[PDB]
Image (spheres, coloured by chain):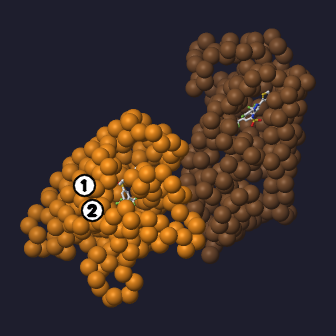
Chain colours: A orange, B brown
Amino acid sequence: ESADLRALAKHLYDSYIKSFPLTKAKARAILTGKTTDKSPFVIYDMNSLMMGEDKIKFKHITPLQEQSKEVAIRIFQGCQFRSVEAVQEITEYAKSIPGFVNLDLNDQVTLLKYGVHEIIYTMLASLMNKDGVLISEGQGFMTREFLKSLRKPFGDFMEPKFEFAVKFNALELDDSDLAIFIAVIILSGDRPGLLNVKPIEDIQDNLLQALELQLKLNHPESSQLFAKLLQKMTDLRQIVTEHVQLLQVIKKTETDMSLHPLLQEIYKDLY
Amino acid sequence: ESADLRALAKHLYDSYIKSFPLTKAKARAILTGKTTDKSPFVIYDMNSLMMGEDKIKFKHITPLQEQSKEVAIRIFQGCQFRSVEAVQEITEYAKSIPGFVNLDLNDQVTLLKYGVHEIIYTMLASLMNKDGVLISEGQGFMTREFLKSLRKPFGDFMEPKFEFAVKFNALELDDSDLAIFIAVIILSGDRPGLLNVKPIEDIQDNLLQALELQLKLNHPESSQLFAKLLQKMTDLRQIVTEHVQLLQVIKKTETDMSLHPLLQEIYKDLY
Ligand SMILES: O=S(=O)(Nc1cc(-c2cccs2)nn1-c1ccc(F)cc1)c1cc(C(F)(F)F)cc(C(F)(F)F)c1
Ligand SMILES: O=S(=O)(Nc1cc(-c2cccs2)nn1-c1ccc(F)cc1)c1cc(C(F)(F)F)cc(C(F)(F)F)c1
């Protein structure tokens, strides 16, 4: 039944709603200017950032990290903290994908480890326009120009993500489309070191049918959107390998210590 | 609500299975016989010690270096390496505790820094009986009468752990009980130097309620088990102060030591 596929789409939207407080629909209204209530703080330069360490921290001192050290470094570390948070959220959502928790425990672990980054860049696009990105739970907005202005290695971090987002966003996907897409990415039977490939493909098969039916009904006038969407999955992998290269350059060339243990042993045979 | 609290237990039990390779179940299987494999190498004197270390012949080099010392200090070296490795495991599991990674970064660090040792000994009981302890992934045993025999300082190290374990093990906790208990340990709002106490206590509260239900549902005949388990937190805090106490006496009677930088930080300014 098509009814079951819609039931599955529906189940995935609701779990997505619970796992991810800042949804695309909310982020876009923020990025535009709907129901004017509490406009976000704008970080457009080194000075406004300084002025802003005490606009997302000073209220009560519970930050992503302390002061001092280069601004490029501080932003880097703040994004470390932020990604481990994104990961817990993605992990929670994953357990709500039917069949996922019943997979071999270590295949769960492998799936998450290779899948999380592609889900971050997909979902970070919902938070982006062509001019910058919502941060601090939609409380701030950091310009693409400022990120790009940071000294050499760190100024190149974000541009590729911005470039992906602009084009991905032109697809006009809504959270109900993204909910199933994110689930398709998780369940990829081609990740390195997976034990049982077939049960993962059997799940991704059902989520592919659901994704297809979703897009046909929700986006009838977008000829071959399903296909276009699956092709973006190769774009995502590129953004990831490229982000992984740059992290390897940073860690080999820089002089700043003590980092987030999460993706530290996860630096072992990645993308 | 009961179902939230049941899901919390279930969640915590999964990450537990994911972060910790030698669980309590599997370990008692090795101590009992219930397992369909091997039989651990018993170390009781200097000769069977000089047997157990060299026994590494079909079980080659473990994550650690070459045993470039003597007897006591030779174990002193390996257990340091085991500790480092348990910490990694405990850090990984902590990140999976809902709300942990959203806390102030410095309080995450402080919570780990104190909580780690308590969880070490708690989980060390799982691998213990009154006669000795599984070491090396449970491929070895190592009598309490051997460990007790050692030199003036090294002679009071595992004893307090064994005595703790004997009584803790009479509580009949499983892996699913222990999953919640260890989370309640890390989320302790009284650790010195904590910056925002209340959000930590908030989470412990929820964990405490989940512990309660787990015990009540899992051990319905065990009178006041909740209270008796939590009383065990005082015992654990004593083992830690004793441990860290020999670790000082060691700096007066022995020569050069030096620790993995992860253990140096973890023992830094520790009561
Ligand atoms: O995947 S990211 O590009 N990671 C990242 C960016 C940056 C920097 C940008 C500018 C100067 S340093 N650092 N990191 C990062 C992330 C994780 C690490 F382990 C190490 C570094 C990322 C960027 C951002 C943001 F766009 F807001 F910059 C946000 C996140 C979030 F919220 F998902 F955590 C992630
Ligand atoms: O926490 S322990 O008591 N550590 C420890 C024991 C011992 C020794 C006992 C007898 C001679 S040396 N040394 N250490 C130790 C551990 C870490 C340090 F930084 C310094 C010392 C410990 C003992 C054991 C065991 F019983 F196996 F000995 C195992 C572990 C494990 F698995 F948690 F790492 C930890």
Ligand 1 visible in quadrant: bottom left
Q: To which quarter of the image does residue B3 belong?
A: bottom right
**Are the residues tagged 1 and 2 within 8 Å (C-beta)?**
yes
Please tell me which residue is depicted at 60% across the width and 56% down the height of the picture: B106
Q: Secondary structure at mark 2?
A: helix
Which quarter of the image is occupied by the N terminus of chain A? bottom left
- In the image, residue B98 sits, relative to residue A175, either above or below, namely above
Please tell me which residue is depicted at 56% across the width and 47% down the height of the picture: B92
Please tell me which residue is depicted at 78% across the width and 36% down the height of the picture: B128
Please tell me which residue is depicted at 78% across the width and 25% down the height of the picture: B142
Q: Tell me, yes or no, if residue A248 can be seen here.
A: no
Q: Which residue is mark 1?
A: A159
Residues at marks 1 and 2, CA–CA distance in whole angstroms: 8 Å
Q: Secondary structure at mark 1?
A: helix
Q: Is residue B9 left or right of residue A112?
A: right
Residue B76 place in picture, x, y as percent: 74, 26
Residue B163 place in picture, x, y as percent: 88, 40
Residue A269 place in picture, x, y as percent: 38, 35
* Disc ID at residue A144: 2
Which quarter of the image is occupied by the C terminus of chain A? top left
Chain of the residue that carries numbered disc 1 in the rendered image: A
Q: Is mark 2 within 8 Å of ligand 1?
A: no
Query: What kind of residue is marked 2?
Result: Arg
Label 2 Cα neighbours within 10 Å, binned few <14 / some 14-19 / many ≥20: many
Label 1 Cα neighbours within 10 Å, binned few <14 / some 14-19 / many ≥20: some
Q: Tell me, yes or no, if residue A85 can be seen here.
A: yes
